[PDB]
Length: 50
Length: 22
Image (cartoon, rainbow over all chains, first blue to last red; front, side, top):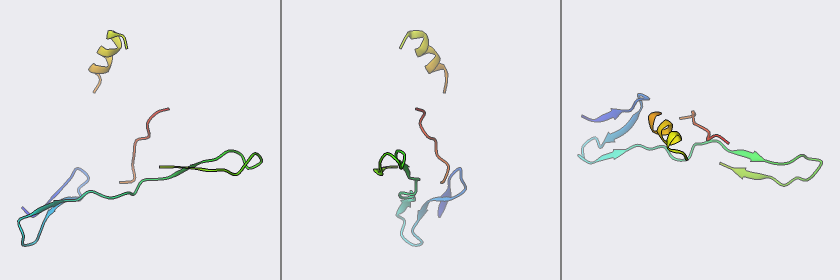
C-alpha cells in the first residue's frame, strides 16, 4: 500500500515514497465566518464568529 | 431528563458542515 482514500475518495493518509513512515492528511482551517452586527442606524460595532 | 426522554435519546443513533441548532 502507498496511500488510502476516505469516504470522500480523497487522499487522507499517504506514506513517504521511500521511507516507511506514514503521515495522515487533515485539512487546516477552511471554515466559514459570519458577522453579527445591529442596524446601521443604531451603531456600527460588529462581531466576528467562526 | 426523564427516563422516557433518556430512552428516546438512546434509541436514536470540505465545504459542507452541520450548524448546531439554536
